[PDB]
Each structure stands twice: as C-alpha cells, then as structure tokens.
Length: 384
Ligand SMILES: [Ca+2]
Image (tube, rainbow, N blue to C red; front, top):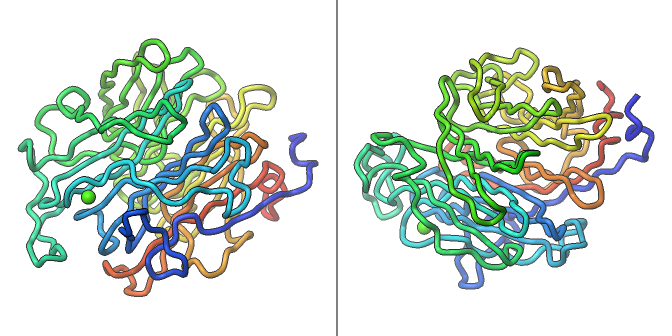
C-alpha cells in the first residue's frame, strides 16, 4: 500500500486566468485584456514561489494573431498558491507587435528560470487563409525567415519578477528548412545528472553547463510528436510521452541523452490528440510519476490524473477523474494541462476550460483553472 493514501484527502480549485467574459477578468496594468487564456505552464522555483504561464489570446481563441505570453506568480515564496488572493496580478513576459508569442515551456535551473517559447509573425498561421481582426488573411507558415515558426528563450534570475528580452534561437535550436514548429508546451526538466531537457517538435533541446550558464543543443528524434512531454523515470532513463497525430492514445518512447528508442502507442493511455502533462513526483520509495491528460479517444473533457509506481512508468493506475472535484462558473473543464509539486506536498495543476459559447468557433472564451490536490485524493478515487 502507498503510505500517502492514509492521509486525509485534500483538493481545492479555482480559476486563475479569467477570460474577458468573466467577472474580474485578468488584464495587464496597461489595460490590455484577453478574450481567452490557453496553453498553461507551471513551475515551482527553488524559493517555493510558483510561476504560472499562459498564452493571452487578445481577440479570439485562435492559435494565430496577436497573442502574448503572460504570467502570474504567487505573492510570496511560502503561500503555495493556496487561495486566489495568494497570486499577483497578471504580468507579461513578451507581447511585442501583432505577433504570436506562446507555447510556454519553462524549466527551473537553480536560481535561473529558463522559459522557451514559440513565435510567429502576426501575418502568418499554421494553415494560412485565416481572417484576422483587421480583415486581412493570413499567409501559411512556411520555411522563410519571416514566415517560419521561431524558437525563443528568455530567462529570469530574480524568481520570475523580471525576464530578459527574448533571444531568437531558431538558427541553432530548430532544424534548418523547417516551417511549423512547437516547443512543449508545459515544462522541461532537470536531470539527476544536472542536464536540462526541453521537449519540442521532433526533438529534445538539451542544456548543458553550470547552473545558470547553459549552452543548448538539439537531440533529433525519429517518430516524435509535435507537442511532447519529457520525464526522467525512477530508473534514470528519459521518457517522451507525446500527443499523437491521430486521435487514440499517447505515443511513448524511452532512452537516454545518447538517444531514444522507437515511439509506440501506449494503449493504457487514451488521448484525443491533445496535449498532456507529466511530473516526476519523487524518487525515494515508493517512486511516483504523475500523468494528466483527457483520458478519452475523442474528447478533451475527460481529464484524469494518474500515478505510476513503475521504474520505467510502463503502467499507470486508473487514477482520478477531475470531475470528482468539479468547479462551477468556469465553463467546461478540459484540455491542455501542466503540473508542479508545491512546497507543501501537493500537486498543483493548471487545466484549460472552455465556455463553448460559439461551440468550436473562434468566439468561445477560454479560461484556466488552478487545482491543488494531494496524493491521497488521487489514490482514494472511487474507481482506483
Ligand atoms: Ca503580440
């Protein structure tokens, strides 16, 4: 038996990024508000402060157009994001121009937080032919310098308070000739041996060097997804657990910094072609890996958090459905997620929610929920 299961269950949940349609919507100090928030990423810093990132999509819920990378921090290093008033007001990492800034993918490295992100020129979209608010039609993302997806890196050495001007690393950390790209979204990791690993489309991005003074390289992968997760399992090996191209199940590969083995579908982890998140919770006995996604082959509204006790994370339990702790007044929960461990031995998770007013159309407002729960809450789930 898992000794953490004997504890009293704990869960608490509330909206952290409140869309423009909601009371007390999240706005920047400049007065800039956002139609939707999507694409969460969360990390605990070495002070205990929590940093929550998202895409602030200004005018509608689409992946293209004027989109800013925004964030909140907990007001103190010690409050663990317990209550809504424990969080600072909305701030911006980068929002310059009419461009798309997004795919936040942070990793904590001692006293430096690195944040990788994707960017495209505001006149371009993944598919092309999309209408922008001014009536212009996007061009299709292509392999030109202006028209491709870029990869940027920004850093903080003051616990997330301020961020360096993002540095364009496309020429060294994205393959030449590539058009569309993505990093994460969600999080990177620091290995037991001290290297940093950031998941990206078709590759890992590897940081080596002393803490806070890293240089970065690509590890090209065969058969990897566009939106990946990375994890160091208790056996010390790396694992990529990726969003599949076709709806069905997660696509998983295992290996080391010298290379990954083949990707293959994991039939224990249904997925509707959506982002997921993964977290190494602890390496001491019993070692646990936590996984969160929508546990369904066709919809995003079946959010499930699970534990694996396997050294290679081969098998996860049923876990618990997040609808067991439902939250009112935030739309229909489900979508992209990100998890961290808090200082008080909870899992903190950001989870997307959709008001669905325009159905799948661009006008449906999107918000992001902050959940905390302990292992007991997962372990003692009714179907677990
Ligand atoms: Ca912008």
